[PDB]
Length: 98
DNA sequence: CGTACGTGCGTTTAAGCGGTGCTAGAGCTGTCTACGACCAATTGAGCGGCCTCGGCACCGGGATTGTGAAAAAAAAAAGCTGCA
Ligand SMILES: [Ca+2]
Ligand SMILES: [Ca+2]
Ligand SMILES: [Ca+2]
Ligand SMILES: [Cl-]
Image 1 (tube, chains in turn orange, cyan):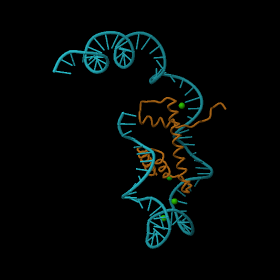
Image 2 (tube, rainbow, N blue to C red):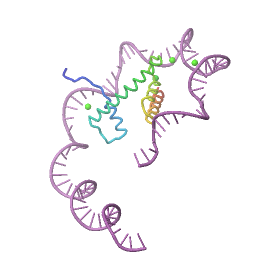
Image 3 (cartoon, rainbow, N blue to C red):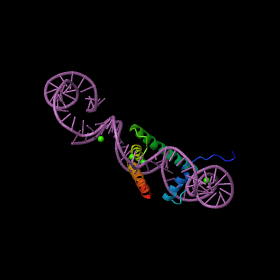
Image 4 (cartoon, chains in turn blue, cyan):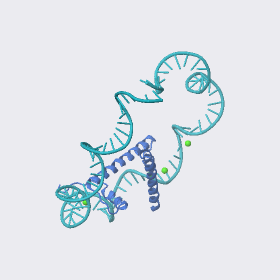
């Protein structure tokens, strides 16, 4: 024993995004806990529906297109437009880096 | 207390029905290869742990903000009649 086991989180990232969006504001541990719950919630919803989609169409593979269709299903209007936008942009940029 | 909405009637409308003809496209098969799993070697990003100091929570004691009472006033209204 002697050292507690490692429990992953999105904290470093939530913080990274925080400095982008507001360089001089911090975040309490409870607030960070809510953010981590948030990310995990949504991960699970999007992956979940992506999972159904693939299975509903007899595909073994969850691709970027299943994420997109799921994102359209789970987010409301404006949020989904921008979400699909950022998702599209990111995959683009990522294939350019090769 | 006033009328909206239920009831019942005569007239009008088009749903449903049974059928026929045409064709998009659902869904299957066979081929072929790009891509994702799986691997072993490599290494850097993120883990837990720990220290510092700055943000925020307290606290007190001063200023603004609404509420309720009481009063004035206004203003109505109520009770009652003159006079035409
Ligand atoms: Ca086809
Ligand atoms: Ca392919
Ligand atoms: Ca830490
Ligand atoms: Cl993909």
